[PDB]
Length: 182
Picture 1 (cartoon, rainbow, N blue to C red):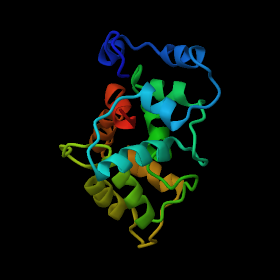
Picture 2 (picture 1 turned 90 degrees about the horizontal axis):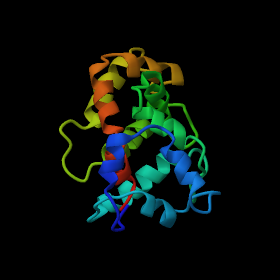
Picture 3 (picture 1 turned 30 degrees about the vertical axis):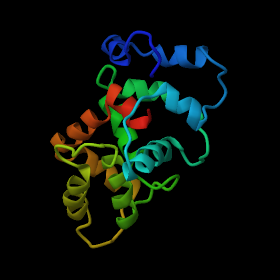
């Protein structure tokens, strides 16, 4: 990020997969703090979205725990866009959107979570996932359960496909980095 060497987008154009290896390979690897993370990623804040792009990005990657970033799935994240990786973006989809470490969907709780993910856009998104999730979410809960298990979320992810692809596009590389933090 920042700095005065080459461009972040330039690296994105190449993108192979081992890039993250360079990350852990370079610098004092062993857990990344918010300050160290923020440098590794760019972003343009202003107000509320400020705490939403940090909390939303850190909250999704907080994987159960929080207060720091534990490098582990970072490679998987790269595989998220690299070589398509449809199945890989599938797992992330569910992983990112649900409660901290609770895969169970309470409808109301997920909704808010999806808002953070859709809140990852400082500018007004062409189509927020919030409305998408609502339409898809409502259809999923045919029995009016009010809650959806991991399996239901997976069906919703596969269903429509087109929307899911849009979410996939949101889960880009340069955009994701910018979303992470300045």
